[PDB]
Image 1: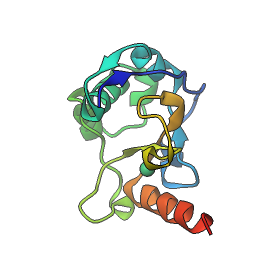
Image 2 (image 1 turned 120 degrees about the horizontal axis):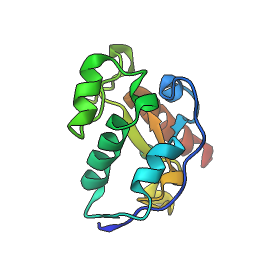
Image 3 (image 1 turned 90 degrees about the vertical axis):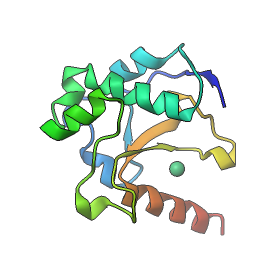
Image 4 (image 1 turned 45 degrees about the horizontal axis):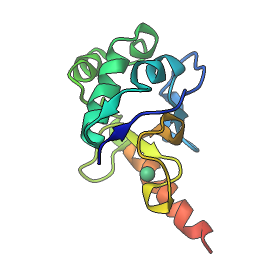
Amino acid sequence: EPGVATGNGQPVTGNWLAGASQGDGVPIPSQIADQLRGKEFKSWRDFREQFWMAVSKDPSALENLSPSNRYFVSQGLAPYAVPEEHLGSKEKFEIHHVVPLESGGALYNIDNLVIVTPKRHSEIHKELKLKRK
Ligand code: NI
């Protein structure tokens, strides 16, 4: 579903992915949002690839990735999370829609995105489901 990205992200210092395994996940750094906002995307896959390429071009965001993960984001691929944070065949950091798409959330609004591990993304959706009761 094609669209235009919007949103600004957050000012982030330090290790921007450390919190991806916990809580609400981590916001998108504003300097990554700046490389995407206003651009048109053909599909979610297109956005995801350009998102990780934007990460690859930012020294601050690259600094807390392993060397192998720096290679992968330079190819527009998501970096791998540690094994304890995998969920079935899902092994890489995921972009989660904070208000889910299925709950009226925006697809390419960067302020509706966080990064989460596969394990934490699944937990967040379980928790959202429970809280409907
Ligand atoms: Ni999600």
